[PDB]
């Protein structure tokens, strides 16, 4: 992240989360993943503020697509988006997070390990490791929208109330990533029917994430409807 244009000007929580994700991935058997049009940096404006986005994306044998995206709208909204899309053959859940901030602080902090099984449960080993973290206390919980049925029972969706809660959230993301990267070492290739089940779950996850009109409006205000539809369906939440 040393070379990032956006990092020095992002919200401090976002900065720490970007660092923690990058550190998680740094020593993995990474290969490039080329986004559409080999996208890296992009900016756009229409009648209002400009939107700037920086994209990084990788893959490993266990992770189809590892996407870390940083964005800023003018000087007033920052975003961090990250999804680790699993290779269905290994049946791992989806790591994701979305952190939205403005000059007044973080408004939204979401993180999850989301299921891909048809029973909508995480694998047993994840259930047990996540439970062992304890129920975190957060003073300003937010209720997921209906499309957020995709998220696990461990999903976080808060407005951090103070620095202690910002740090607690970051630590929980670090703990999610640690669990995930360990479970990826012990995963074995699954049967064809199980692989297919997991593929289905990933497709459903992406179709539901595309219902987030808050994200879509940010994109539309800077680039228009057609660009935003392409970005959400081809860059952010591609349907395999
Ligand atoms: C250019 C990219 C990008 C932008 C600009 C972005 C913006 C964005 N995401 C939001 C919410 C949200 N975002 C999520 C969740 C997620 N979203 C994800 O991209 C992932 C991976 C998850 C979860 C793992 C949820 C659940 C909400 C709340 C939606 C709502 O309030 O209706 C909001 C509303 C913040 C608030 O209400 O305080 C904005 C503006 N998200 C982005 O990804």
Image (cartoon, rainbow, N blue to C red):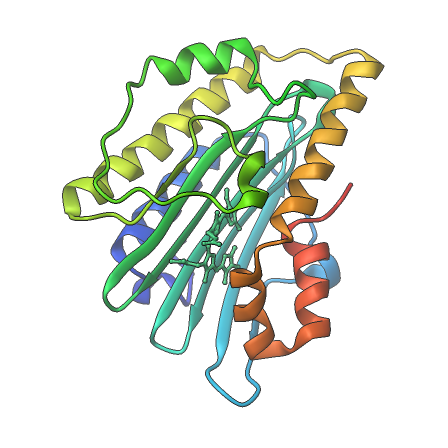
Q: x, y percentage for residue 32?
A: 65, 45
Location of residue 55 by image quarter: bottom right
Q: x, y percentage for residue 117?
A: 66, 21
Classify 19 as above or below 222: above
Callout count: 0
Q: Is residue 208 left or right of residue 3?
A: right
Residue occupying image coordinates x 56% and y 78%: 222
The furthest residue to the right: 192
Q: x, y percentage for residue 188?
A: 67, 11
Classify 202 as above or below 238: above
Classify 57 as above or below 232: above
Quick one: quadrant of the C terminus? Answer: top right
Q: Is residue 20 left or right of residue 31?
A: left
| Closest to the observer, 175 or 135 | 135
Residue occupying image coordinates x 51% and y 39%: 96
The furthest residue to the bottom: 47
Q: Is residue 143 left or right of residue 223?
A: left
Classify 74 as above or below 158: below
Q: x, y percentage for residue 35?
A: 69, 55
Location of residue 206 by image quarter: top right
């Amino acid at each position: 992240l040393t070379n990032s244009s956006l990092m020095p000007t992002l919200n401090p929580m976002i900065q720490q989360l970007a660092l923690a994700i990058a550190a998680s991935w740094q020593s993995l058997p990474l290969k490039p993943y080329q986004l559409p049009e080999d996208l890296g940096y992009v900016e756009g404006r229409l009648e209002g503020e400009k939107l700037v986005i920086e994209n990084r994306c990788y893959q490993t044998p266990q992770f189809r697509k590892m996407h870390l995206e940083l964005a800023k709208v003018g000087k007033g909204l920052d975003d961090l988006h990250c999804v680790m899309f699993p290779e269905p053959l290994y049946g791992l859940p989806l790591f994701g997070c979305d952190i939205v901030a403005g000059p007044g602080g973080v408004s939204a902090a979401i993180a999850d390990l989301s299921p891909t099984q048809s029973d909508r449960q995480l694998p047993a080993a994840y259930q047990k490791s996540l439970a062992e973290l304890g129920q975190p206390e957060f003073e300003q919980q937010r209720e997921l929208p209906p499309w957020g049925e995709i998220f696990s029972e461990y999903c976080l969706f808060i407005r951090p109330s103070n620095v202690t809660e910002e740090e607690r959230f970051v630590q929980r993301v670090v703990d999610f990533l640690q669990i995930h990267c360990h479970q990826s070492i012990v995963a074995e290739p699954l049967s064809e029917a199980q692989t297919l089940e997991h593929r289905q779950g990933q497709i459903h996850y992406c179709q539901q994430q595309q219902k987030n009109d808050k994200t879509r409006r940010v994109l539309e205000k800077a680039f228009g409807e057609a660009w935003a539809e392409r970005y959400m369906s081809q860059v952010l939440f591609d349907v395999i």
